[PDB]
Amino acid sequence: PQPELSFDAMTIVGNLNKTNAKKLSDFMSTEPQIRLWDILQTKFKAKALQEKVYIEYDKVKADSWDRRNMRVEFNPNKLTHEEMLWLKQNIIDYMEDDGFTRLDLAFDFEDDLSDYYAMTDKAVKKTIFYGRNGKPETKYFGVRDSDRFIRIYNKKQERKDNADVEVMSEHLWRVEIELKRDMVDYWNDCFNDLHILQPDWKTIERTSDRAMVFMLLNDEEEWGKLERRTKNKYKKLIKEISLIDLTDLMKSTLKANEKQLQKQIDFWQR
Amino acid sequence: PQPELSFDAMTIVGNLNKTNAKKLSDFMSTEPQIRLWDILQTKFKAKALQEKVYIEYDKVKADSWDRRNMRVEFNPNKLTHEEMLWLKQNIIDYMEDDGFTRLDLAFDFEDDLSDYYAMTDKAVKKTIFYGRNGKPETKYFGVRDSDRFIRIYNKKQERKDNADVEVMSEHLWRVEIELKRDMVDYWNDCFNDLHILQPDWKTIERTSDRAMVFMLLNDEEEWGKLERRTKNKYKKLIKEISLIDLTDLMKSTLKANEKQLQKQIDFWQR
Image (cartoon, rainbow over all chains, first blue to last red):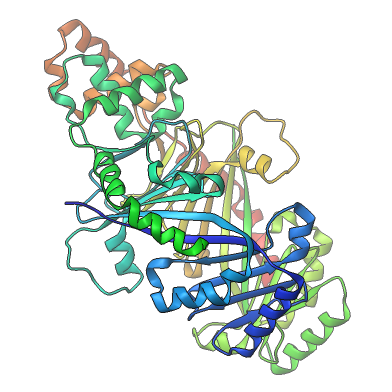
């Protein structure tokens, strides 16, 4: 099936007038439905819309480092159009120099991806959480504080664990692609290096090759020991080996929805 | 070599009088060298000894979980005898029902443990943090909120990352054993189920060799592809190879230091 695609988090950074700082700070105090703390004239913090939006202002940090002085954070999938309009009119519009600092792509699949092998052709860090079973439940590729980070994990299990309403599907896995700083502008093709695979090594006829791969695919630590020219050889081979690569479906769904998603972004920037 | 062993964290939980709550709350306010916040009559938080000791009191949250109402947290390796005596006299003594909630065993090794891994006789959950190189830096066995949790990680790398003074040894790895709640009393012979192992093939110097074996050990059909002259080379190699189990050295060092460690505990409970 085609995976559902959506933005899953958005950060927006901007700068705020002396006049507007207060104006906005003033406004917020009057509304009991917003939660205010860490207040000074140069500082404030806030959560709004039943704690779905984080809002932070700090000028002295902003002056200390040559940066923008207000962030707004939230997940658009959990906001109501009504709400989105409220937030734009009452917060975002009053920011200047405003743009995106974060942007997350969420591909939901109704398959089980435990059984796929997820890989980057690039030489980066990883993290794997295994279940009691010895099988993987959550995978991270890259590091969170970076231009690009990827999670692949069992959404069903994660939703169940979070006491969310249970799901009609028998399997549900997400593939989240966190784009920060300048990478946000390339969201429409950000999983070029990424592949989600599953091959059948038997059908291959070179013997040492098959062993070597089989090991790489069954002890992730063994990548750590391999010479760099070697790493590339086996990266090549892995990709070269598998029939169905879900990358292709992702790229497709992305293209199919590029225009809507694009509009959805444009909305915030006007 | 024999690994250095020590307790690496201690939590102490107790209960505090109405009288003593204030008394202590009063005492602390007078010392500018201790940092007080989140104050109510039922609540208070504090860090002392240059932020090395956390201290938290909460009556409303003690009973709401059916526990004792004050924690004191700290790493004994980073405290001065002077300091330890200060803390006992000015804090711990005024607690009643006092006992240990947490206790961590730290085995430092001057070897490289990258290729070693732990297994209980259970198939518990796991976490592995890999470096950019593809090698493992940190391994977790179990879950942190439990009677028992184990970290094995590169202390050298972790100390370097923490901007600690660099170390004369070329390798330094720790094996931390976090014991909580009732398990603390059994710090002393846990390893009937447990082994810190290196599998057969891991022990080999040679990448191609170790791959080839791993495959032979995990796919029966791969013998069928191999002329006899090869089979023997790997037959030879297999027999030639043993698992290394560090458990034994740990049990030993533990026994060797049981009495000191035991005294070191007794100190706090008087």
